[PDB]
Amino acid sequence: AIGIGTLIIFIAMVLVAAVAAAVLINTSGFLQQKAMATGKESTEQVASGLLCS
Amino acid sequence: AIGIGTLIIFIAMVLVAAVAAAVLINTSGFLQQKAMATGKESTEQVASGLQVIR
């Protein structure tokens, strides 16, 4: 009797961990974009300019 | 299930990192004005004066 249930709830544990992992993976992706963008943009700003002759 | 907590603590971690970032942005603002003014003022001081002709 006991065995049956153990299997079923095991399935849920798997799926719930999977769903949580998805958040972390995705979010890391979402941040990767903006992280890079900010650095490149900021550098180009500080480095560039014009000078009156 | 372990996943549940992992989610919840992430929410916290983000929020704390936000607050930490904020103080630097704010402080940089405060310092900006104070610095700029100090330079301007000091410059005008050295540059200016009067001379007795006769």
Image: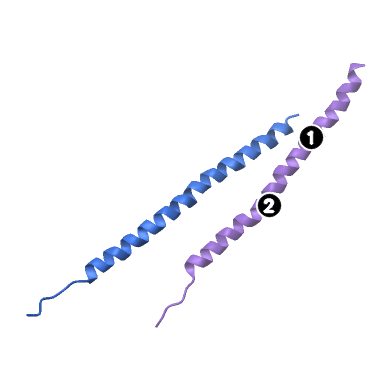
Chain colours: A purple, B blue
Q: Residue furthest top?
A: A1
- Residue A4's x, y, as percent? 91, 21
Which quarter of the figure is the N terminus of chain B placed in?
top right
Circle 1 SS class: helix
* Labels 1 and 2 share a subunit: yes
Which quarter of the figure is the C terminus of chain B placed in?
bottom left
Looking at the picture, does residue A42 appear above or below residue B49? Answer: above
Looking at the picture, does residue A34 appear above or below residue B51? Answer: above
Circle 2 SS class: helix
- Residue B40's x, y, as percent? 32, 65
**Type of amino acid under label 1:** Val
Residue under label 2, please give it: A30
In front: B26, or A6?
A: B26
- Residue A32's x, y, as percent? 65, 53
Q: Which mark is residue A43?
A: none
Report which quarter residue B8 is drawn in: top right
Q: Earlier in the sequence, mark 1 or mark 2?
A: 1
Task: Tell whether label 2 touches label 1 (CB within 8 Å).
Answer: no
Counting labels gives 2
Residue placed at 83% from the left, 28% from the top? A10
Residue placed at 65% from the left, 39% from the top? B11
Query: Label 1 crowding class (10 Å Cα cut-off): few <14, some 14-19, many 20+?
Result: some
Residue under label 1, please give it: A16
**Type of amino acid under label 2:** Phe
Label 1 and label 2: CA atoms lie apart by 21 Å
Query: Does residue B22 appear to the left or right of B6 in the view shown?
Result: left
